[PDB]
Image (cartoon, coloured by chain):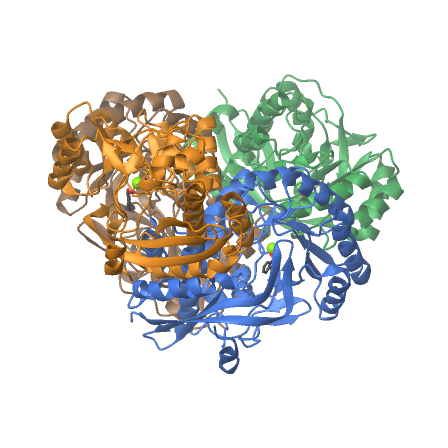
Chain colours: A orange, B blue, C brown, D green
Amino acid sequence: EVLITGLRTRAVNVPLAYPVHTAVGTVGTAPLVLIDLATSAGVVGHSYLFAYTPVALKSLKQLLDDMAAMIVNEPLAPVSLEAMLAKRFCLAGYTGLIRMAAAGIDMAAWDALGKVHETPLVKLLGANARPVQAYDSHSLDGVKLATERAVTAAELGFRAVKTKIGYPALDQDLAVVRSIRQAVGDDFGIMVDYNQSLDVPAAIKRSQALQQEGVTWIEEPTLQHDYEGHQRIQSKLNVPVQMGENWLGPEEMFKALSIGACRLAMPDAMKIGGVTGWIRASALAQQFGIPMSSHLFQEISAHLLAATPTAHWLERLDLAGSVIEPTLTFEGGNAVIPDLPGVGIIWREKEIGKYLV
Amino acid sequence: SEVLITGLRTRAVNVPLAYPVHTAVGTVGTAPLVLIDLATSAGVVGHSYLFAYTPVALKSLKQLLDDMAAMIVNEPLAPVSLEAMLAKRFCLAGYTGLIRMAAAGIDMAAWDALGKVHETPLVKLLGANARPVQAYDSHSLDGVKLATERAVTAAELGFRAVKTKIGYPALDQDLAVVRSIRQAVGDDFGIMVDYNQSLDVPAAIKRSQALQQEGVTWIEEPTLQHDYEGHQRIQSKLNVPVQMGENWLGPEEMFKALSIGACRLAMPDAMKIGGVTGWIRASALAQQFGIPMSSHLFQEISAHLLAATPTAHWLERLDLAGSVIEPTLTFEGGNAVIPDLPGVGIIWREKEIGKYLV
Amino acid sequence: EVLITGLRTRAVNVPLAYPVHTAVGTVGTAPLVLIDLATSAGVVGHSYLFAYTPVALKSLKQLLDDMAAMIVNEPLAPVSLEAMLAKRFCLAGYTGLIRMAAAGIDMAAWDALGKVHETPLVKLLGANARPVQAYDSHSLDGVKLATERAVTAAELGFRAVKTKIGYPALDQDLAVVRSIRQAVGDDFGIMVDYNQSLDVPAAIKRSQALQQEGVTWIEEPTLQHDYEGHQRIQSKLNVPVQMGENWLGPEEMFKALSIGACRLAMPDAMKIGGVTGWIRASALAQQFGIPMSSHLFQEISAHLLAATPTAHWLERLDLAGSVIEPTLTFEGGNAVIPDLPGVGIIWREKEIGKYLV
Amino acid sequence: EVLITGLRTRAVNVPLAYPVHTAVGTVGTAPLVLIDLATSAGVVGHSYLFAYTPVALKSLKQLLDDMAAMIVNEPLAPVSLEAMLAKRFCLAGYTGLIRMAAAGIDMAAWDALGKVHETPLVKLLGANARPVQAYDSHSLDGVKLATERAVTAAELGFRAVKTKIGYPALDQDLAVVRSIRQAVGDDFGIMVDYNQSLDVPAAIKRSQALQQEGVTWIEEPTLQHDYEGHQRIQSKLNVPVQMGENWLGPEEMFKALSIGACRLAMPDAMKIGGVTGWIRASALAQQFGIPMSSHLFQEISAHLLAATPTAHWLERLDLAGSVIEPTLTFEGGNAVIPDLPGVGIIWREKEIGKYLV
Ligand SMILES: *[B@@]1([O])O[C]([O])C2=C1[C]=[C][C]=[C]2
Ligand SMILES: *[B@@]1([O])O[C]([O])C2=C1[C]=[C][C]=[C]2
Ligand SMILES: *[B@@]1([O])O[C]([O])C2=C1[C]=[C][C]=[C]2
Ligand SMILES: *[B@@]1([O])O[C]([O])C2=C1[C]=[C][C]=[C]2
Ligand SMILES: [Mg+2]
Ligand SMILES: [Mg+2]
Ligand SMILES: [Mg+2]
Ligand SMILES: [Mg+2]
């Protein structure tokens, strides 16, 4: 019926209103690959990828462009497409940039499929649209900016914020949390994120002090692939350890959950394998008893969380707002899925040319 | 005197193979390689190459490496510190896959350059005597007739073992190939077999128990490479050793596989394991877990690396880059012999490389 | 190309400015074996061994001298030499004094290889020299001397000290830590060392009390070979248990890490097997996620920690300062590797004669 | 109160009628340290140590001579003396040559204590003398000599022999076992010993072939300290894996038995820690359900096995026959304890002089 007829990618470097400072360096702009998936039915699927660093941006575009011949003239059947890519790349390594590229095609193909059936992605997945609580995602901003941004988020109606920590001293971590807490009050979430910057003993010492201060979760305290080390950290805490943005495919999530690395999970729509990977991830989170949040890609994560049995929070970090129309809205701090077929992404074509690499 | 990296040059080539590498999951008909030149303030140039597996990833890998150049040019030629830096710089994007392979290619060129700085073969720089290492001639999913011809030819060349790739539609076809080779080479000869991830766990148990009755030397990647639990289940049903490791991206994946008991043999890939720096760490693990450790591809550097490996087992002879690298590595009586050259011993065939440029 | 041509050893008993009092007895002098490895390239490798007690000093020298014929005329290839000694001693027992002797040969051979290549050992290992934070290592000194020494170390720039505890009463342990803490303030490390003197229940009781006071780590609470007992102790603590100075070879480290005996490790350059053993130990500590410190042998440990992914602290205990030129220096508490080939050891040939046994 | 009044040691290098060829090299002579423990009761305890290689011989004697100051004038209480040595050596490392030296003192002290009470050692331990089945211990002798020695062993009355294997080819291992089996018949033991020479997959392969041939046990297939690896080999076999000659102290035995490394044990009276360590090893083998044999030191092992609840075999390898009187006899292949106080060791004083080092 519906065949894939073309793939077009555009690499952009988009500035951010606030740089994403982390304990391991600053992401000052967002390197994105914008994807269009043309089909024989007249509709075009849209998705985008986040390359994290300009150093990988051109590499990821080139890879996608060389993948185009693998998918042109195949049926628009994302689950069957994913299994084909999984096999074709099983020698090179179906991980990293390659898996990220495969997820970008998956997310565009699902967008295309909802458009074919003139229906929002959440409904094509068999679920009712529902609002999801969102937290406003901040960075390693220093006490002054961290507190201003938390006040502005609370004014916009958000009920929780995330700040990135891992300053040179534990006292600086605690100063930021304490200052946010005094400005937003007790009935407010403060999630904190170390971006893999602590070894396991440091993470136990810092995390127990944060837990005494009162935080909502402690995210990626150590090396993201060290599932055992996260389990050891989690074993010393009442507060939940959060991880998942760096799981490449549901199989990595299965490994982490099988050994108890974390009491929360937050897969990333790209790295987990797109919609197809998210659905599988969501089935694991349910059976392991893990409340499941999103990481980035807030446009598509609104739909996916609505179909997730243990949906927890949506991360509001609008990486692509400069090139995507704001059809996703926030009422009372909850993300509200737009009444649009597919994901609801509409390119801001006038702005894209400003940021092309 | 301090030695600095002063340039990084890459060349993407798509190189002929006398025999296409047929596998159960598809055919590698040419070798897409990225050749790496690491210029230094000592004047010497470090050489290495990467294998992209599919032409689909070739240009992307070269592009990534060219964009990584800015991270390493004007840094000290200290491969262990360079590796720590790349690990940190890529911890958000994902220090795995193509990025990790790119980092390993830098690492292998940097260690080559450091051996050249000290005018000494890499094995001796690593603190070990050069020793010959037994090598098996590595074949593919060749069908009975060609599989048998290549095994006879390898036996005449002095090899004492061959590897064939299996996973034909029927187990009887796998068996027909292994049996035909055995009849042509005799009883005092290794036959390693390679499934390239093509079986589920119950099929792998069934096929491997039948192959075990034929006395093959090991059974390589029976199922999905990341499925360490499943490999353990397959190994639990076998006396023959399960072999894996060519797809471990970094020694951290090796550590996870060995921790669960996935395999009684290991064969890291000098590229995917993370280069010389990653190989040294992999060898330390294999030693403590009691795992005989073989190589995967990259025979030029693997001869050096195995000589430094306490549990060194076999060298895979698959000469992917022979069309563009001078044959300074030799084989005597089936054993790889390290050349008396500084660093790794790689000398480009500069007049051949231009024939294959992408 | 380069062969070992000779081995010379000298047994000394050297005075210590401060006796090393421990919970299990006093090391009042340092019995050392000083090692010279001659090569066909004109350079001489240097190392030394610490015998812990004069009772073992002459035995260790004799053993090394009887090992000379095994290594003379072998290539200067420390990794292959270690394999040869491992095999040759596999029936006698490649542990204990024999293993310590093998490590002494290894450290001198690596010094000699760096000298053949005219490069500091850290650079021959492929790493940049970097300063390494050091703690000043004290002993079971009693409240008065313990505090004085802690004050003096703080004045010299050290950011942490180690004291040895295990007085008859736990109150005496706590009185020393409290006194040191008042003199150095809260932004200062206090590591404490029991030297195997407690059983597991006593160690749980004392360690929880020291944890409440605030210490940096608790080292060797019980019998060094009792990895399961250390695991039980560590399971009851937030503060990290530290061990490793008694691991004979990385295979013993592997056993202890595999069962979770400690959250920190500190291998001893001699007992772990010299440079070759150290390299293997550091690969394990990295995969197990263990910050790795040194025990004694500060001259060579400065190089080794600079090549160690999880390098933590250097122990500053200058056992050999009376016979080795102070080319290793300390700036702001950090050990600074000297710009010398190999390890940087230069014998004080006038002083050695004063201490020969 | 009987006190120790002297400690005398003599290093000898004694001839072997048949060199002990092994897969890892040849022990052509026996380097022994002969021990005399004089007491204030006038009786003298006798024991001896085996240094395995002449390279360790003078070092072991030197260490014993320097330990003498720790034990002279102490009461003749072997269990209290062992505890003192354990503590005094806890920093240097109570293993290796130091532990072997401590065991030699322990074995002389117990022989001394038997003499004080004019009673054989077995009776002082509270057990009846009973004959213990012995196997004649051979080496890596090749097909011709291995079979000749097996014939001669059978004619002397032994009902089992041990041969050492680990020839370059598995077919050579099997050719030896097959020729011995033809010469001795089916109702006869053939123990085989690899002396650590195989990796784990090679050991699985050779052992399953030997198991098909029919052998009594498979001894030290891989590295002696690799307890996990021995467990993996044992998991693939019906035939029992045998080890223990290299355990230094019952604490190492405990670690191996705890993980299931072997279904048989054979501690070495020296390395296990003398009579004191043997008694503790016997208590462990009993609870773990492990039949327990001896390694070497046949003179004292005859007494110790008589007191061992799970006593299995005595290794007959008469390393010291050139310097000790043949008071131990063999009836029907069973070792028969002599009716003599203590261990029953009487030096051949006119012979020791020929072999002094
Ligand atoms: B951090 O992990 O939280 C944000 O989503 C983010 C982070 C790092 C880099 C970019 C974005
Ligand atoms: B196979 O795994 O063995 C060879 O090394 C090879 C394989 C697949 C693809 C290329 C080479
Ligand atoms: B103790 O463990 O710390 C010191 O390094 C030391 C110790 C005991 C004996 C000598 C030195
Ligand atoms: B072997 O393990 O059996 C014998 O007791 C023996 C061995 C090795 C070295 C000496 C004696
Ligand atoms: Mg995060
Ligand atoms: Mg393979
Ligand atoms: Mg200590
Ligand atoms: Mg034996």
* Residue that appears at 40% across and 64% down: B106
Is residue D320 visible in the rendered structure shown here?
no
Position of B239 relative to A42 (above/below):
above
| Horizontal side, residue C299 vs residue B263: left or right | left
* Residue that appears at 65% across and 41% down: D220
Q: Nearer the viewer, residue D249 or B191?
A: B191
Indicate the position of residue D82 as horizontal and vertical percent values.
Answer: 49, 29
Q: Residue A312 is drawn in which quadrant?
A: top left
Q: Residue C217 is drawn in which quadrant?
A: top left
Position of B78 relative to A114 (above/below):
below
Is residue B65 visible in the rendered structure shown here?
yes
Q: Nearer the viewer, residue C94 or A161?
A: A161
| Horizontal side, residue A312 vs residue B260: left or right | left
Indicate the position of residue B300 as horizontal and vertical percent values.
Answer: 54, 68
Q: Nearer the viewer, residue C250 or D346?
A: C250
**Ligand 8, image quadrant it occupies:** top right
Q: How many marks?
A: 0
* Residue that appears at 27% across and 55% down: A349
Indicate the position of residue C118 as horizontal and vertical percent values.
Answer: 35, 70
Q: Nearer the viewer, residue B151 or D270?
A: B151
Indicate the position of residue C301 as horizontal and vertical percent values.
Answer: 33, 52
Q: Residue A236 is drawn in which quadrant?
A: top left
Position of B207 relative to B136 (above/below):
above
